[PDB]
Image (cartoon, rainbow, N blue to C red):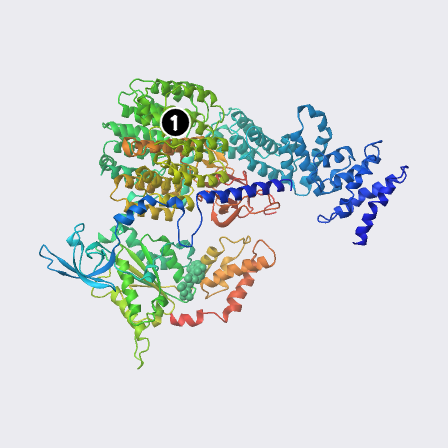
Amino acid sequence: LSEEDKQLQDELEMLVERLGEKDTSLYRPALEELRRQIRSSTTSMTSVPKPLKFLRPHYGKLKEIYENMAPGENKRFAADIISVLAMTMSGERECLKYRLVGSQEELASWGHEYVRHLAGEVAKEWQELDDAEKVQREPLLTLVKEIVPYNMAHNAEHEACDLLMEIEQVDMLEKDIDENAYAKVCLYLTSCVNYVPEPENSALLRCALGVFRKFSRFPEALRLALMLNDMELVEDIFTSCKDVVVQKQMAFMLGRHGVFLELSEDVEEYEDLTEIMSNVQLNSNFLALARELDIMEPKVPDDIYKTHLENSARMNLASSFVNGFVNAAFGQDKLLTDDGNKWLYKNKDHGMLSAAASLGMILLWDVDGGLTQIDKYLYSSEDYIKSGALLACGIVNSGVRNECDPALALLSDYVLHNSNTMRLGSIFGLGLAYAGSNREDVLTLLLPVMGDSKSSMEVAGVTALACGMIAVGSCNGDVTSTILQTIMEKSETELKDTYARWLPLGLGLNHLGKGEAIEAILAALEVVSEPFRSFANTLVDVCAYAGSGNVLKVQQLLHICSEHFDADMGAHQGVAVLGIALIAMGEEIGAEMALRTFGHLLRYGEPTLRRAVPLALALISVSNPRLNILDTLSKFSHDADPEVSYNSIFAMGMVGSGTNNARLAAMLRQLAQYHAKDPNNLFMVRLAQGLTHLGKGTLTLCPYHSDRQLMSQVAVAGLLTVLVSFLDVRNIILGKSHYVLYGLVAAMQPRMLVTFDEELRPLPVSVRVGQAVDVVGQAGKPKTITGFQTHTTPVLLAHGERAELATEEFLPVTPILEGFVILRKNPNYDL
Amino acid sequence: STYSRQIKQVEDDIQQLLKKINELTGIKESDTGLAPPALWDLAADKQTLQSEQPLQVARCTKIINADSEDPKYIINVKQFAKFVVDLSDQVAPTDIEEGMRVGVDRNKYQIHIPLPPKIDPTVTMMQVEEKPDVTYSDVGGCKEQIEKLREVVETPLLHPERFVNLGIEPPKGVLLFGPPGTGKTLCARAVANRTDACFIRVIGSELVQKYVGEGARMVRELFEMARTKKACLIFFDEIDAIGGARFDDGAGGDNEVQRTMLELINQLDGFDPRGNIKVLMATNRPDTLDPALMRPGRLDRKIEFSLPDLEGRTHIFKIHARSMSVERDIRFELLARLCPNSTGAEIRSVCTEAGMFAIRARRKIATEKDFLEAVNKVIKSYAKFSATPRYMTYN
Ligand SMILES: Nc1ncnc2c1ncn2[C@@H]1O[C@H](COP(=O)(O)OP(=O)(O)OP(=O)(O)O)[C@@H](O)[C@H]1O
Ligand SMILES: [Mg+2]
């Protein structure tokens, strides 16, 4: 027993004796010392007064002192000691109570560990307090107006967000946000938006939006606005800024997301602002990029196939995709521009449909020049070539929104053309040409096509697909009425056709990411017959929660996969598997947690359930050639089930889409040898080889940009169109309808880092490119990249690779160094 | 600390859930080489154990009366016995040739399947399966060296059409020689990274074997397995281990290793055509190589990796200081001038030590003084151990 410890043990009696005297003259010196006695051990975080822990039973002698008389100074310091004794035990409605009723001095005077327990209490009791207890939060609010300023002072900022998120009072944070912690507070709660549910989903973003708006951080304010798909807030964010240099950067970000803004002519620099966001200069910027990467040389599919190292209508049609994919959006090809007639006519039947349309894909984003080349095939007498050239115009204008509209003009005259093939090349052309536009002009011109008597189910599906791309995530009322109308007007036998599966996607596309706005729509799907209703109900519900990660919805999806049927009744099971990927593609934690569940569907599953899980892997990790999925797919390329073999190989290509992975190409080359005598499997192998060398490695199909935080409506539409068509790979992809593989044209974007001057001209500087590192939590300045290297700016960024400027010569307009970035001279630099 | 109690509660549940998941799925053993149950096709395995009989590996020795309708095959079943057997009815008579390994059943020993030629497991491991992370952009000052290297070892395989039309037979051999640290293996690592054909890395010391004639055997099986590919690349790093010149010192000095070199010479240019193999040898002691090995048709191109010139040294400095946190005005041309005759290996170390001094001073940016001290420590202080002066006489 230490004498100093015994000295405090004496205060358990003699100081209480001083507080036991009737006169108040001895009350204050003992209590004031007792109040300071706590601070004596509070100066050390580990040191606590153990004799004080023996004073807990002594509160009975002090019970009347802090309760039975005036609260001036007798109860003031008497209760606070009990509060100090209250973090030692459970502290249910006690630690706060002596704090609430006792002294109302500065909170931090009692210790950082005390308030941390005190802060943990105020949230715990907040949930317990009901509506009738609103009179009980008067001192409760005062603490949080002082707890939050205390937390930011000692770099314990992340605890501050934890306080007012629990009490659902995130609003008051912005008033006390300082310049030294605005990024740290935003970076933390924005990372919580991937898991917290509605209504705290939007609300947490709104508070982060307010902080950025308050601190004039416009580029990162606009990023938050798009994530909330607030059409109104986008205009307010855009026009609030006065720095015109700052504003053109948004149009680059806004154009990359595919959302159009109709600015007023009164806005200064109106022209270039529209030009930048309309991606009209994307072709020149893309072409100038690859000129710096000296890959302008066209590539033959043989250079991709590498058959010289290897120890038909399908072959010619397969190589048409491999041709176009490799030099997509490049404008030059050694195989189609140079006497294309022999190659194009070397294909047969619907092979010429895709072969002709492949010419529009090598002119992707080349709206002006690309239209100059398809016209030669636009006058072809053969039914397929013109219609293939029709869809080629839509591919050419896909992803580019120019002011005056060519694509509608060249294809409007053919949406009611008597031959279905001529029609077929029209709607899919318009769908790609105006994906993510919500333009009523094209929609109203396209809407009666689905209701036509001459329109077959093949034409009926593409109209829903196309109209879905134009009105993706818009919840357009007009398209919902007609898509529902068509769905129930079709027969029981008519819905048996797998092309009928596309009508729900058009309805599902319209509500992409909208959430709970489907209960009215889902009620309408009740009236339609089975098993199409179960498929339609599952699909549209999935597209509703795309990129949301709502586990409750995924809980329903796994239950649909749980009950197996001894095909026809289990067609909907494939969509549920694709649903898990489409829902969990939001955050990394959910996506990787979904990979293991995909393996179990890949183990306990039935054929129709197991045929779609390769597609889920492609959607969940497109353009992300991670080894875990590739090895999972590699084992299952040579599977007994033909569709699983077909789907897995295609998934490998889409997983490595545009990555130009040397390891993946070696696997695909080996798969070509294994599947040489299987034309169907080899067609999938050939299809994958074209995708992995997409755009000569300068393009990506990943729907996410802005540090994998922004969801692109058009890209998911392009992907969903392809993978939902792959649920019947025998009849659609391998059949006569392989033009649906041109849906991913809507998902083609360049993995770009081009830094521009304030006058939009190229500005090559040294940058650091490496794998991104989470910067949540740890204070100070933690590095956000690991295993990084230094390149000049016009470099292709792989999935998950962040970029930081190596030097400080230029201050980026936006922290996110992706796509086109405007650089400004740093005034402190070269002081 | 407020969530500490709840975090451990959910962390333990996850661990309990993880263990419970492993109870149903099954993640165990892994010491008898058992695969995870997701890949277990038990129904098929039972069928394979009955439908697919095991086959014993045998070598055909002679075919008796091949012209007639009763062709009889003499097989050598390793250490078991020799049998005169007939061919199975599910394989063609023309598919079995004398001297080729075959698979025979255990009952009547009839040949059931032809088999690939036997290759030493060590020789099989010599082919590169994961390419290096080095490109030609990481080699500086070797512009002429690389173009000569590429147009023999890369261009013919990439674009063979440009040589057949003109009736051109491109060289099938390149010798890289120079002092240590000059980039001989660095260029070969760039070749393997870029190549699309099979790449086989063979270190000369790997060809030295305990027994007589074993080293020449591995050279035979090496070229046998290289010929099983449409186009192949063999890299002979440090060929001076086995490529030494022949001599007679009375005793049998280096007689065994000379035979390995004689076998390598025979496969490169002998009675038989070599094939589509394009060999590539690197040595820092080319003066020790046999004249027969250093002859065109075996080593057609002799690419010298001399120490870089001022432009080359400045280029290597740029390559190695690319990812560094260097200052503004690092006079890399001046640093290249401070090490007149220095290999690229020294330049890389100068870059490493230059940033190593900055780490020493708790500084995040390497200054020009740090490089000046690094040059003194590497080029000057470590000039006692420099391999350059002794090895330029050899090259
Ligand atoms: N031309 C060069 N450009 C850039 N770095 C170089 C160059 N030459 C050498 N280096 C660097 O120096 C190192 C020396 O290793 P390297 O394999 O090139 O040596 P070497 O010439 O094969 O030597 P040795 O004869 O001892 O086998 C390389 O790993 C590389 O990092
Ligand atoms: Mg070496």
Looking at the image, the residue that sits furthest to the bottom is: B250
Please indicate whether residue B28 sits to the left or right of residue B326 in the image.
left
Classify the position of the C terminus of chain B by image quarter: bottom left
Please indicate whether residue A156 sits to the left or right of residue A192 in the image.
right
Residue B309 in view here: no
Looking at the image, in which quadrant does ligand 2 appear? Answer: bottom left
Is A557 drawn above or below residue B366 in the view shown?
Answer: above
As rendered, which of B324 and B142 lies closer to the eye?
A: B324
Circle 1 crowding by C-alpha within 10 Å: few under 14, some 14–19, many from 20? many
As rendered, which of B198 and B79 lies closer to the eye?
A: B79
As rendered, which of B225 and B379 lies closer to the eye?
A: B225
x, y percentage for residue B48? 29, 48
Number of numbered labels in the structure image? 1
Classify the position of the N terminus of chain B by image quarter: top right
Q: Quadrant of residue A23?
A: top right
Q: Quadrant of residue A320?
A: top left
Q: Quadrant of residue A373?
A: top left
What kind of element bears circle 1? helix
x, y percentage for residue A452? 32, 18
x, y percentage for residue A828? 61, 45
Is B166 drawn above or below residue A330 in the view shown?
Answer: below
Please indicate whether residue A699 sits to the left or right of residue A147 in the image.
left
- Which residue was labeled with disc 1? A535
Is A400 drawn above or below residue A415 in the view shown?
Answer: below
Subunit of mark 1?
A
Residue B316 in view here: yes
x, y percentage for residue A21? 89, 39
Amino acid type at mark 1: Phe
